[PDB]
Image: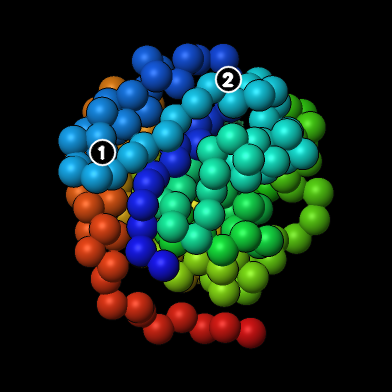
């Protein structure tokens, strides 16, 4: 499959997707690409981001399919990874990904963390996995970001000063997406 759109799945919280963080700027930049689309919608259950709510929304309302690049931020990165356990997607770009509820009640209530990660299913369903992470992220232990990188064999873009990626512009992400639009050579991953 060749990629036809990106979908931004944001972090949890009530910020309007179009005007909060980098989502709107990235959408606008991607929409400059001739023939390309970028969907970004306010999510149902935006505060707790329940798996049982976000994943059906991603399927039916964001139309996430084998021609989609899913760009997931924080809770949205988590949702992207669970989505890829059961759906083929073109690529996933994970910004501030992690693996556990980090002892947070709102994270636990999401349902994303109540069983192990099906890393092999994700790798099988998604041929291109790119990851952004920052060592100074105030929410995430580096070890959990590293766990995602190791288990999904991601192409890791490791920064020291981006925190939880909450700035308004994100050029490095545009570059990544444009690189994926060329349908780059498949890299060797380990499938079990
Ligand atoms: N998941 C939150 C960030 C967060 C991570 C871990 C614990 C608490 C909060 C977000 O989407 O922004």
Secondary structure beneath disc 1?
helix
Tell me, for residue 1, which label it has, or none: none
State whether residue 165 is above or below residue 156: above
State whether residue 167 is above or below residue 174: above
Mark 1–mark 2 distance (CA, rounded to whole Å): 24 Å
Q: Nearer the viewer, mark 1 or mark 2?
A: 1
Residue at mark 1: 30
Q: Does residue 188 show up?
A: yes
Residue positioned 56% across, 68% down in the render: 125
Residue at mark 2: 13
Residue 96 percent location from the top left of the image: 46, 43
**Camera-side residue of 29 and 37:** 37
Residue 77 percent location from the top left of the image: 53, 45
Residue positioned 44% across, 52% down in the render: 68
Residue 100 percent location from the top left of the image: 68, 47
Residue positioned 56% across, 63% down in the render: 88
Quadrant housing the C terminus: bottom right
Q: Does residue 141 show up?
A: no
Looking at the rendering, the quadrant in which ligand 1 lies is top right
- Report whether the residue tagged 2 is closer than 8 Å to ligand 1: yes
Residue 122 percent location from the top left of the image: 59, 66
Secondary structure beneath disc 2?
loop
Give the mark nearer the N terminus: 1 vs 2: 2
Which of the 4 image quarters holds residue 3? bottom left
- Report whether the residue tagged 1 is closer than 8 Å to ligand 1: no
* Horizontal side, residue 186 vs residue 110: left or right: left
Category of crowding for the residue at label 1, using alpha-carbon neighbours closer than 10 angstroms: few (below 14), some (14–19), many (at least 20) = many
State whether residue 80 is above or below residue 91: above
* Horizontal side, residue 67 vs residue 77: left or right: left
């Amino acid at each position: 499959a060749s990629p036809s759109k990106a979908v931004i799945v944001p972090g949890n919280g009530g910020g309007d997707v179009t005007t909060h963080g980098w989502y709107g700027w990235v959408k606008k930049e991607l929409e400059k690409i001739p023939g390309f689309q970028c969907l970004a919608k306010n999510m149902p259950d935006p505060i707790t981001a329940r798996e049982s709510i976000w994943l059906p929304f991603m399927e039916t309302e964001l139309h996430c399919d084998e021609k989609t690049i899913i760009i997931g931020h924080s809770s949205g990165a988590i949702a992207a990874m669970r989505y890829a356990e059961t759906h083929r997607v073109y690529a996933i770009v994970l910004v501030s990904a992690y693996t556990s509820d980090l002892g947070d009640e709102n994270e636990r209530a999401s349902g994303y963390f109540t069983r192990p990660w099906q890393w092999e299913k994700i790798k099988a369903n998604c041929p291109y996995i790119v990851q952004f992470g920052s060592t100074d992220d105030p929410f995430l232990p580096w070890k959990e970001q590293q766990e995602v990188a190791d288990r999904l064999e991601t192409k890791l873009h490791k920064f020291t000063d981006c925190g939880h990626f909450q700035n308004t512009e994100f050029h490095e992400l545009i570059t990544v997406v444009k690189s994926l639009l060329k349908v780059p050579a498949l890299e060797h991953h380990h499938h079990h």
